[PDB]
Length: 503
Ligand SMILES: [Fe+2]
Ligand SMILES: [Zn+2]
Ligand SMILES: [Zn+2]
Image (cartoon, rainbow, N blue to C red; front, side, top):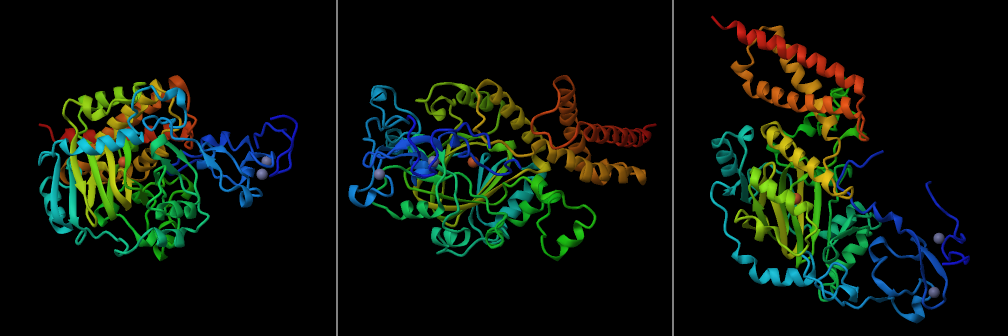
């Protein structure tokens, strides 16, 4: 406040500062609108921006009495707000002490832990529990394989999944050693249901302090597909790499084969690649993550390297979506979706070493009973194309009813389908025509996937005519049309081929 200057950047209050897109799960870059919002040292009375105060994003709102770096030595560490309303996200404000218990809050979680064990077990149709990756491959295949993947699998022993994972004993320490101590990761302030920045070192610091945890901290994503060391340490199961649409257009390879497979443009621009297939996840015991459907209706692999998780899940039926949509778009904050989900929500525990494989659309919330380290990834695949498009409808509807903009959605979702259609699907059809082949013979799966995907894209084209292109852009209305035109052309030819067999 006032004319006075900043002890950090020496600037007097100017300022009004408007001085590539996100391809990975990030939500902390939003309240950078506070980085230049002035806090004052209760001691030397010097004013600091915030950024300039030595504070990290996550501690901006924590302190009632602030002591800047130059004062800490003799003043002590800054004094935090008193915990006045443990049952509210704004735990610091007394004006909210009388309001209802909010789903994310400390009070709510503690109580929830006493009653959570009464959430029903899933039916054998919802989840399948196998001993190792060999049994998974056998049962997965016995239900139609990836093209027909509908239930979640829990694999107890990772042997056979062909899934590259660090050896037990691997922990947070190794993570910070590899990524660096100054690597900033999006962290969820569980009790405040909000996401902030935090040095990876700071997190480790807080994580290791076991007896004193005023707040709980889990990190959002931490996607490591671009860290040359990490990216080889934990990988998706082979079967996931073999069906991942992103992996099909931006193939992993990145070795000697990379030089060659891009020597034919079989590798799209790296900045266009969705960055969501390899994430590391650490969480404190007592943590809770509220019900969500994974972005783009992406499938998930989820390996527990350390600790235990309890997942609360609900099958992706239309009613369950409708119910979920209402819950997401409602202002109510005190009701647990499970309690109003007409009995759909089930309970499943995942222990250390165990793995979770989740198909498209499953609604799920997560309880973290024990300090945890997890490795996982999100992927799209043709076997779940319909469900993926259904979730995308759901998301797009939810996005119109409440102004999220902080909510993360699948990066380049549409671009990816244009590319996939043009590079992969169109060629199969084009070629199958060049030989007068009836795709139903040996490629029914591919034929059906093309019609479904095309219909969805036809809807995107028309939307783009009536309303104009999207902000997300990246592919030019013209190119989009040329693609569509060519696709219609080939699908017609293949249709006539199929119809000729009529007599
Ligand atoms: Fe999730
Ligand atoms: Zn400053
Ligand atoms: Zn000071």
